[PDB]
Image (cartoon, rainbow over all chains, first blue to last red; front, side, top):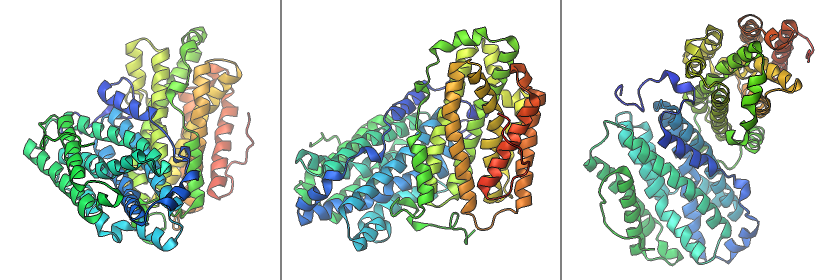
Length: 281
Length: 281
């Protein structure tokens, strides 16, 4: 850890200039420029849309939201307890500081959506505590949570795992909502999904950049395993627990998209693709 | 700690709705609405102003900046390692998430100022590492740093200490810069000082609000000690180490202002004033 420029003790840590890593700095600036608030998303004309939806379509979206309701919180919780603490590089901590801020806005946004669509308190509580009620989302959350408590796994392994959490675990639901946008539905859901994804792409790229700034990191095979594990969990989620069929989507093309996203991560990480499949959308 | 609504285990921690504490929520929303970036501060017309300044006046400001250069970083470092981790209440973590984000912007801003005024690298490094070169600022920083490492002091005591760090330790330099604004000088310095102070007032109020949400907290006498200690350190800083006289200020009226700010904190905390002196400005 003492040979790690990213994790080793840094006395200049508390001051921003002079910049040491312009690559990390530009990452933070892109995030800064992407700032937005939940208030900026107009959900006035969305309750009616939720009404028009079909019983199956609402079942889907409600469940996608159930998982998103706590997902960003889990991420932030890892950033606070681990990443932002571990990393001693000023510029990196700035990026993580803004990511934390944005994850909470994301978290707020999903709560608003659920609040806007579900008026029944029974269901509301049900979806709000999905990590304790919906085994569908319980699995994904537990996967993420484990990496936070894992006091053995290295930052290298853990940063890769969260790159999967923010990329692969978001991918499936992201595409589904993009699908609705295509079909011209739920303008609130699709608009925030666009903003959130822009942040998500940044959080993922950064994770890969931190990876590159790591000297002693996991071997390729270990990275392929972590990524592949996330891929399978996500596929199981959107083809079994909550089939994209419910909203008119091919479960097979969805499975392929996830792998495509997985491949994008591997490249960003500096490795070869695993699946070698084109984006089916 | 298990009887502390703020620090006890919370399973709903990862989700924002339903809001549990609207008072904490409104604090976070005020902060959100106050968002700004360093880029927004035009420093184009400030190098000339720095030129016009008198040798004594620059000596002052340069030293005030020396302390501000790492002060926000130290705060953020406590927020990450302690406060944001300790507190389990969702709304509080949102406020702390945004505070972290804003402290880094503050940190960036001070670095820009120094970068803008001091072209000589020798001096630059000197001021950038003031916590290791300037005993004037070394004392204040060490005071703050101690509360971070103190594994005995309670959150109650520690939150009070940082309320002093963000209030009393900022007060003296704040007033001095406000003084320059009055004299119509350093438009960049004074403009950012206004934005920063707006955030600072929020960080302080919040600290006091968290204090109120604490059940078992330090006794009044202990709060008076912590606050009084900070007051003296700040006075010593601006009447001995770096006399406000250098910019045409009465060292006695400055000492009184600090106590006035100290008294404001005590009230916000729910206690009686200590000094009972009016604002001399």
